[PDB]
Amino acid sequence: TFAKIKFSAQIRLETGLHIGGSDAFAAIGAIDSPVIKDPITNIPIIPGSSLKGKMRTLLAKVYNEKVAEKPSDDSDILSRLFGNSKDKRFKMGRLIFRDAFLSNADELD
RNA sequence: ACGGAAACUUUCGUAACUGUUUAAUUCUGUUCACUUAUUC
Image (tube, rainbow, N blue to C red):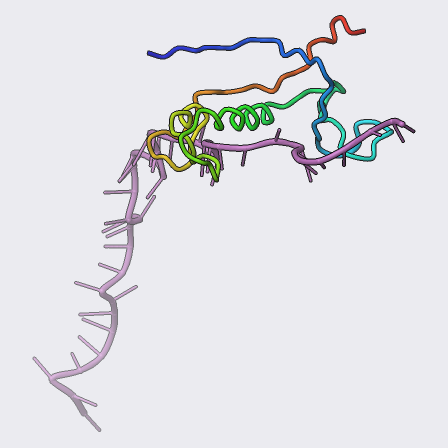
């Protein structure tokens, strides 16, 4: 009737990425867009907005039936997984992500 | 050298007792700080 499925995993980075954050003040040697971190502490963290915006794009190009043009209006077979602000049959999404935090500080030092 | 002369409709007493503009309601549904790039 109503179940809760939590996909707990550990994202391992094999190659250093580069995602721009807010302002260019993460250190004393920046000149371009740095990396988003934590407003309280000083640990490089990755938000959850970049995961939904990238996984949906790479998935809607093989599981679709029509050439897309605008978001929330392509491939109805997967629109119920992320959401749709135009279809009256559903509005809320059934896939809630989470801002991944760096928990590798217990053995990095 | 008047059917006149003498004289408070006056004294007393809250329009009063009682009583929620109340019950119900996410300012949210879609959204990578991105694209091209030999520290040689």
